[PDB]
Amino acid sequence: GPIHIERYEIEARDTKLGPERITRDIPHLSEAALRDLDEEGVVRIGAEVKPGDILVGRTSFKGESEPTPEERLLRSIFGEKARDVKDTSLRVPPGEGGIVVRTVRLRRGDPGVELKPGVREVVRVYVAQK
Amino acid sequence: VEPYIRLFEAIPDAETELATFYDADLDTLPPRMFLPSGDLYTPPGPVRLEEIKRKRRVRLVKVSIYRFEHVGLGLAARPYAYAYAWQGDNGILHLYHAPVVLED
Image 1 (spheres, chains in turn orange, green):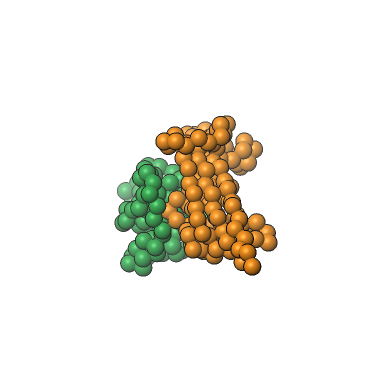
Image 2: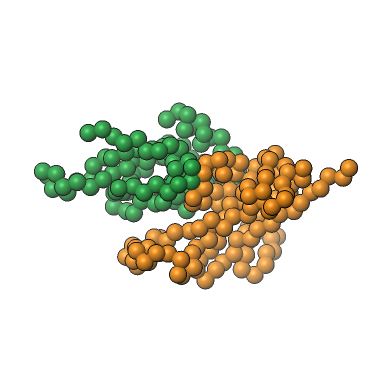
């Protein structure tokens, strides 16, 4: 019986709306949903992941017509720091899951690292399927 | 406080750069706050933070929740509630419990 190891991947890229970021600091998520994430937002080795569970936390800035009108005013008034990010995390797909066995994280500008044009960072998670 | 130090320190560590956290104040907009269920918590005024512990990308804080009132001495920011929380590098507050409302 061969063990099935999946390779999951997510990129945080530069965007016209501002940078995507790999992080643990994700809005609208319960403590339980964040439970197995390291301080970077990357799921810990040894964790059991099931469909819908987070492997890698990510947030992105919202599109133009997403915020409410009051939220558009607040931005204009208080500045570009008064913007709400949204949850764009890497989640375990339907019908998959298992145990996290390895992670890899690379950052643009580190020595020897060459990422796609636009990519600030990339994280891969390996899961041994059950 | 101590059980919240426990929860916080159980966040797995990682070699990364130190983040610069958002020191929210009576002067500034409070950041988005969430209860442990994931529900948005909307404060009735600004907050102040007191750092208890920190790692690289997250810190533990005591969050003091204020409300404005027009008492005898004019406009005042007055304490309304408090909650322990962790804060991340988007400045977001993740509450460990619903805020405890302070008795007058």
